[PDB]
Length: 209
Ligand SMILES: NS(=O)(=O)c1ccc(Cl)s1
Ligand SMILES: NS(=O)(=O)c1ccc(Cl)s1
Image (cartoon, rainbow, N blue to C red; front, side, top):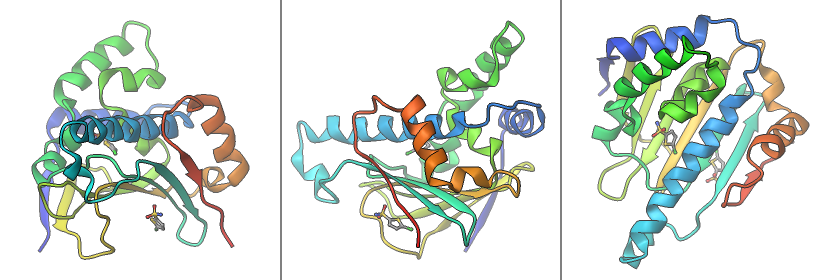
């Protein structure tokens, strides 16, 4: 059972701007998704401060980066608060309509795409490097779901029958043919050291073969 949804017009406009605008500094996608993961980990930690059972689904709070050259995917895993089905449909838990509005007025006022994160819609910078994005998520109050979109105006949501997560969010980036540099160990390490050196959670870069 797979449900298909239309993006709100403003969000469709944002993703086409990200996909079509010439902008060479694509590496900021990773900073934005790691920062999103850190925000989600902050939220489950705060909730657990007054109710420890919120961590029965997983005590460890961390971020993993998993490149896979065979599948040409880069996956960002965190054990944060996760997302409900309603959250996924609701622009992945963001205020994306008002955020896109403020972002686009900022761009005509001197901004560039790199401050997308200041407007709450940093997730969509994933489409600087990915032709398709899959999001697997598990929230304590809901079941495990999978979100997917290749842009073009629509996204899908289905119950995920894959590997159980426990709690958190998995962003799978199906990389464009000319963006495979972000599967290289020394290139990921350079970006994490440049942009994410102060994230308050352990970031583990997996190796291959
Ligand atoms: N869409 S979002 O809520 O910024 C987000 C992307 C990845 C997460 Cl973990 S949370
Ligand atoms: N260690 S983990 O983040 O659960 C993971 C290992 C392999 C994946 Cl694919 S996801």
